[PDB]
């Protein structure tokens, strides 16, 4: 069933017949008489009604509403456009311990000015090293430059005028949105519903600047899920990596503390942050454990193949999740995939200088066992030969 | 042997995309600890087409819809279908073919735009694994852009300004893909194919905007009703329906500048 | 950095576009004067109409409703009928099409507030004798009786009922989109009701045996509804006086319908939490 | 029930009459019988239609009144689409001499239902001579659900045994398309305001598990109260599931439902490893069958057509009855009395097989068959006693 | 008994239907409990916890009125059943 | 392209009536102590068409008159036929179709006027039950 | 269980009878069904004692 807007000719005839039958008693409508003008004016008023109605009912449809009408009936439901963002990064400063600091620090790296974004301590730490979080003063993509050396804008007593940025990484800059891209992602959001699935929380942490990977606690960690007298799980914790910024991708505790407060709120357990009400959590870093790998027999393979094996092994260890065994079998497979199953390959894992490192232990099979809060970091890969062939 | 200027040529670009995708996508040769991720991405890419098709044919109840739906479910459930580059490409190409023929006209605008949005990501792996994953994204976006252009050719241009605005939306996407393929001679042949297709698209989209109904701006001496305007310009008040979509303002206050067709007595 | 603003997805950053100017005129721009004289241009042209069409005048009577002014030397003609038709469409559009569009959106409905609630299947939890025992020993609208507590059904005046129902509809529409149940999002959802949640514990928590929240008023006035396409709504009081309405003395001095609806919504959202407690505190107008 | 308020007809007709006089006739009213009277009346008639047009064009936009086509268009905007038809599915065992080549157009048959391979068949039979395939019904619909274990090849191929057997289970999962009205109620349910949607979300999700037919919430008899006399509301999530098309009476063994629970909630539960969100913990239950014999009395006077339908309706009602719910004589009497007529002399009784006691079954004074928790009333036999009347 | 735990919309329907049925009841005819119970089941559903009872106003004695064992109301000749007041009570726990 | 002005259009109104009749007439949902009365009314409505047809074709002796008469008798004798809105509408519509084609011209004036007379009553039940009648 | 049909007809001494009512979908559980039949052709010849 459906009734729609009538066509012009089918509409005038309806009026003419109705007018003639009821008013003139069946008399024909002679053109150019007064009744002729009455009929046509009546029809005009009829058509203007439908035309306006159809025009107006389009505006309430988001797929066709004008720009100024889309911003409304979109802020009503809690969706707003996005303005220009700011770039962010990390810096390091040193000086005489105990010097008084200020909350108005400014850094000039190269034609760009950056302002402190975190709370600066009142006095410099005892060790004489401090790491901050800074954001560009002018929003836009131009704040993503890659420089490693900068200077403090204004001198401060007891603090050097030279500062460095970890890895010269500055990410986050972007421009404002346009009308058309905003129309999408709104009528697309109408078909979405968040659910707090662990994947959602994991994806949320990656929005922090200079974060690359994220993993759950490894097999060698005994977690706690109660945190109170509750019936079933209540807590969640997971690691983070900064592969492109910090050495080995591991950040100092000063940074992960900030992430934990933002994501889970402060105080925790009351849904002050981005997490669900009544859910507590924590984000933790790890400490590096250095290793050395001695590949045996690679020297007798072609130079091209040798480099590929070295590159693949280095990449795999770099991405290894914290607190997880680095078994020998995994390394051997990488060699077989490229060198062929018939090659005389062999690998071994030893600590630098054959010393003892906290959180490291070797099992009978030759693998490396790593405890909680520790990660396998590659220190050096070397090729040795002690056999004969060819 | 007169030339044709009423439809696009999609066969050349589609074949060009096939070669580029097959060149790099190879889950059986990439390093073993990345095959699972690469395959998983492909399964997601097909799912995007599945969602698009199901949305377009909501009210269809023919016997063919059941068969197509069954085919989509069977392929996704099977785990070995995506190990073969030949199988992977065929499912991708055919999926869009069903998507394009599901509906005609404006109905496909939203569906295709969403797919383009999803295919704007870039892989974060290293070396070969990155190429095996970027191929899926790049191939999907080019196919969606090509089919989006075909959709625009099936609707009347409301205005010259709007018609050209639609064209710019396509040229930008094709230009971005061309730069990626030519970034470091990643695929020289693909770069040439994209460049030639873009100029072909321009030859048709520009013609549609400027010459489909051949609109022109009139200059009336004051606001007047839609019915009167239609009668004066043409000579048939029944044609006022056309003026509704191209001119703002209420039906009783159209003007003082009107946009209409060219009288070709 | 930017200043975040509340949003359905939490705290986000807002911005503005630049004016376009391609918006079709809305109901507001239409006026009886606008088009009453307009149809004088639909008539033909010639010596029989030139004088009549030139001398067309229109004036507004007491209650709007443009009417042609007949001077001492008025010459009757069909032009008078054309003006009459103009007055008709302006009136019919207002009485017929404007209400139809107005009631179609939950954020603008005025007359059909009650009907909209039946669409959402909303049922208040403070009006059923078999209420959940977790809802407190004595609710604000229950007075103790020998055979257990008994509730009283209030008959609110018209204006407050219209405003309260309108506010409830807005919040329900916002919630149907789905949200992540954190404090920032929840406050935004029930924001139109002029109620805010605030935890009591200020320390770390997460170990204590109970989590307690309380409701604090943000304003003493609902946002009224506006019938006309223009203007602004008239605020109305969000509270009710016990004595004025001649209710049993056992009830609290002031009764806030808005707080009650907000409390029910939040309780349902956070039902899965096993240690959620509510400590309602008496509130009075400023 | 109108949404557009319409003033009283007398008020309107005065307004049109007043406006006409002021504008055209210069303040004077109309003569009772003249052209001015008739044009005024006609103007009123067209006004009524305008009101209806606005009323309809608003009505054609609300989900609970829109046409059968505009409804699906609206549902697309919110990501809700109708369910298409389904095909049966299952596994089939094949035996033959090794090395013989196979074909892709192979088809089977189990009790008049033809099945075809739903996966890429290998080139030739493996060395062991046993092959396992995935099959789908050639035609959709619920007719593809059958409970059998032996079939026969339809297209003979040399070197392959003419007899083919399925797996221990059977083929199922097929279903018919979704009509318009069932779609409308589902769409409205999503839009409406419902407390504890997490429970509803899980209940809907469970229906996607293969072979599942119905989902029942905990029955009234499953309520419990602590020693303090206060009703206890648990914080877990639980419900029942039935397999009417696969298991006798639709009750499955414990091992089957254990697998569903792990997938839905994860292992260990609550850590978000399953389909449920983080911090969600529950359990899926099953039920045990208690037999029942039902006797219909006084049905001889009814015409044979009436007797057949009354017996059929009662049989369906018992079959679909949820677990942990009482079965009262009133319900069965009402169903039959609704067809025969309120004045008919109709009576029913319930008794156990051999009048022997069973677990979780108790007869109260009124004749109801009270049932404990984790128990479902399973029909055993419908018998209509015989008498003599109307001779 | 028990209607208080049903939705307000359903509660009114049951009250309205029962009142209408008794108003139309023929004179000098028994008003059995089963008839009232059936009205409730048709709308509330077969799985609802429903119950009804009939009592005289003030539990007094009225000429031509008696109650049988089953709980129905017996009415003699020249007498009719007239509704005086319908009330809802709750004495159980659920939800 | 020309228009026709020699015949009426009955397909639109008939389909429009079908929707309205199906919308309200639902004997399986009306309160149980009114289903019998509603169904009885429907049986009377069909009987009126049956009487009209038998009057128009009195002198016919074709082989189709016997079949139509048998069809009318079977439907009324069977009891469950009117429990389905689909069945009820089909009988009503088809029954009129046979009535219209029974005779041509003035012969149908009296028959149709009588039926209109019978259908000027209004139900005296209450609530939704009144709508079903 | 066996499905039924709508066009089935019987025979009793050269007289063929057809179902005169809506046949059910399939045979009931007890395997016994009762039908209403009418002669295919009218006239007194349809009366028989068998």
Image (cartoon, coloured by chain):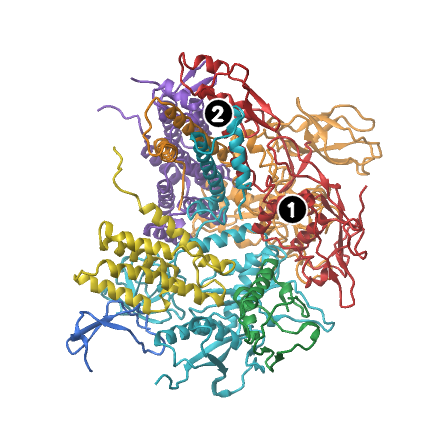
Chain colours: A orange, B purple, C red, D cyan, E green, F yellow, G blue
The chain to which mark 2 is attached is B
* In the image, residue E50 above or below residue C232: below
Give me the residue at 55% from left, 54% from top: A328
Which residue is the site of mark 1?
Answer: C165
- Quadrant (top left/top right/bottom left/bottom right) for the C terminus of chain D: bottom left
Point out which mark residue B211 bears. Answer: none
Say whether mark 1 and mark 2 are on the same chain.
no
Q: Is residue F71 visible?
A: yes
Depth order, front residue of A377/A261: A261
Determine which quarter of the picture holds residue A103.
top right
Q: Is residue B30 visible?
A: no
Determine which quarter of the picture holds residue B230.
top left
* In the image, residue A91 above or below residue D212: above
Q: Position of residue D358 (x, y in %)?
A: 54, 83
The chain to which mark 1 is attached is C
Left or right: residue A205 versus residue D127 is: right
Q: Residues within 10 Å of mark 1 (few under 14, many from 20)?
A: some
Left or right: residue D10 versus residue B81 is: right
Depth order, front residue of A216/B216: B216
Q: Residues within 10 Å of mark 2 (few under 14, many from 20)?
A: some
Instruction: Report how far apart the C-alphas of labels 2 and 1 lie in the structure.
Output: 36 Å
Q: Secondary structure at mark 2?
A: loop
Give me the residue at 18% from left, 75% from top: G46
Which residue is the site of mark 2?
Answer: B248
* In the image, residue B249 above or below residue D201: above
* In the image, residue D195 above or below residue F73: above
Q: Position of residue B76 (x, y in %)?
A: 42, 52
Left or right: residue F75 versus residue D353 is: left
Q: Position of residue G32 (x, y in %)?
A: 32, 78
Q: Secondary structure at mark 1?
A: helix
Q: Position of residue C77 (x, y in %)?
A: 45, 19
């Amino acid at each position: 069933c459906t009734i729609q807007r009538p066509e012009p000719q089918a509409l005038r005839d309806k009026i003419a017949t109705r007018f003639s039958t009821n008013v003139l008693g069946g008399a024909e409508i002679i053109p150019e008489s007064n009744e002729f003008y009455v009929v046509t004016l009546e029809y005009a008023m009829q058509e203007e009604f439908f035309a306006f109605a159809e025009q107006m009912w389009r505006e309430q449809d988001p797929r066709y509403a004008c720009c100024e009408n889309l911003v409304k009936m979109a802020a009503r439901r809690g969706v707003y456009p996005k303005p220009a963002q700011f770039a962010q990064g990390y810096v390091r400063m040193t000086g005489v311990p105990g010097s008084a600091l200020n909350q108005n620090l400014r850094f000039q790296f190269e034609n760009q000015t950056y302002e402190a974004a975190s709370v600066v301590p009142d006095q410099l730490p005892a060790t004489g090293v401090l790491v901050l979080r800074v954001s560009a003063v002018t929003p836009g993509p131009s704040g993503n430059i890659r420089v490693t050396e900068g200077s403090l804008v204004t001198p401060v007593p007891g603090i050097s005028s030279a500062v460095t940025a970890y890895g010269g990484n500055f990410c986050g800059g972007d421009d404002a949105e346009e009308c058309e891209p905003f129309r999408t992602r709104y009528l697309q959001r109408l078909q979405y519903e968040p659910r707090l699935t662990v994947e959602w929380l994991k994806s949320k942490a990656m929005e922090w600047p200079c974060v690359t990977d994220v993993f759950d606690l490894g097999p060698n960690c005994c977690s706690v899920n109660a945190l109170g007298e509750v019936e079933c799980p209540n807590n969640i914790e997971f690691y983070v990596l900064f592969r492109d910024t910090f050495d080995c991708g591991l950040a100092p505790q000063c940074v992960v503390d900030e992430i934990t407060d933002w994501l889970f709120g402060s105080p925790q357990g009351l849904g002050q942050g981005e997490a669900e009400f009544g859910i507590c959590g924590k984000v933790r870093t790890a400490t590096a454990v250095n290793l050395d790998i001695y590949l045996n027999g690679l020297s007798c393979a072609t130079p091209a193949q040798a480099r590929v094996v070295e590159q693949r092994i280095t990449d795999f260890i770099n991405r290894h999740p914290p607190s997880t065994n680095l078994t020998v079998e995994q390394l051997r497979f990488i060699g077989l995939q490229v060198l062929g199953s018939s090659f005389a390959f062999d690998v071994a894992i030893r600590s630098p200088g054959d010393a003892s490192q906290s959180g490291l232990r070797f099992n009978a099979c030759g693998d490396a066992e790593i405890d909680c809060d520790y990660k396998a970091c590659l220190n050096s890969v070397q090729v040795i030969n002690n056999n004969v062939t060819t | 042997l007169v030339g044709s200027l009423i439809a696009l040529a999609l066969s050349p670009i589609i074949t060009a995309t096939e070669e580029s995708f097959k060149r790099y996508y190879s889950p059986e040769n990439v390093r073993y600890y990345n095959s699972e991720t690469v395959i998983a991405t492909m399964a997601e890419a097909v799912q995007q087409v599945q969602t698009g098709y199901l949305a377009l044919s909501g009210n269809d109840t023919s016997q063919e819809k059941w068969t197509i739906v069954r085919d989509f479910r069977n392929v996704l459930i099977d785990e070995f279908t995506f190990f073969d580059p030949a199988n992977s490409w065929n499912v991708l190409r055919n999926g869009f073919s069903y998507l394009d023929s599901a509906a005609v006209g404006q109905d496909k605008f939203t569906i295709l735009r969403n797919i383009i949005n999803w295919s704007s990501s870039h892989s974060e792996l290293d070396g070969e694994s990155a190429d095996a994953q970027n191929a899926i994204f790049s191939a999907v976006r080019v196919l969606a852009t090509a089919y989006l252009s075909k959709a625009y050719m099936e609707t009347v241009a409301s205005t010259v300004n709007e018609g050209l605005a639609q064209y710019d939306q396509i040229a930008a996407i094709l230009e971005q893909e061309a730069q990626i393929a030519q970034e470091d001679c990643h695929d020289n042949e693909f770069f040439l194919s994209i460049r030639e297709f873009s100029v072909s698209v321009a030859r048709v989209m520009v013609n549609r905007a400027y010459n489909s109904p051949a609109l022109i701006v009139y200059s009336f001496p004051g606001t007047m009703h839609s019915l009167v305007v239609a009668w004066e310009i043409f000579g048939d008040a029944k044609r006022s329906r056309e003026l509704e979509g191209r001119n703002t303002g209420a039906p009783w206050a159209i003007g003082p500048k009107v946009i209409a067709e060219r009288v070709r007595a | 950095m930017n200043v975040l603003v509340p949003g359905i997805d939490g705290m986000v950053s807002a911005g503005k576009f630049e004016y376009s100017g391609c918006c079709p005129p809305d109901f507001a721009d239409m006026d009886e004067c606008t088009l009453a004289t307009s149809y004088v241009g639909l008539l033909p042209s010639g010596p029989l109409w030139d004088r009549a069409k030139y001398e067309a005048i229109t004036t507004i009577t007491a209650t709007g409703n443009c009417a042609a002014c007949w001077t001492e030397d008025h010459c009757p003609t069909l032009v008078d009928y054309a003006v009459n038709v103009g007055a008709r469409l302006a009136s019919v559009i207002d009485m017929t099409l404007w209400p139809a569009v107005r009631e179609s959106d939950p954020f603008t409905a005025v007359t059909s507030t009650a009907d909209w609630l039946e669409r959402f299947k909303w049922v208040n939890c403070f009006e059923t004798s078999c209420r959940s025992k977790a809802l407190g020993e004595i609710t604000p609208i229950e007075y103790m009786t020998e055979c257990g507590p008994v509730y009283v059904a209030i008959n609110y005046p018209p204006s407050i009922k219209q405003a309260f129902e309108s506010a409830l509809i807005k919040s329900l529409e916002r919630l149907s989109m789905g949200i992540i149940k954190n404090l920032a999002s929840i406050n935004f959802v029930i924001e139109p009701l002029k109620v805010r949640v605030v935890p009591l514990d200020t320390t770390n928590a997460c170990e204590n045996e109970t989590l307690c929240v309380t409701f604090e008023k943000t304003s003493d006035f609902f946002d009224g509804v506006n019938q006309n396409p223009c203007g602004i709504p008239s605020p109305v009081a969000a509270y009710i006086d016990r004595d004025v309405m001649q209710l049993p003395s056992e009830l609290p001095k002031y009764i806030w319908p808005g707080h009650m609806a907000a409390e029910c919504v939040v309780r349902s959202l956070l039902s899965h939490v096993s240690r959620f407690c509510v400590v309602r505190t008496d509130q009075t107008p400023d």
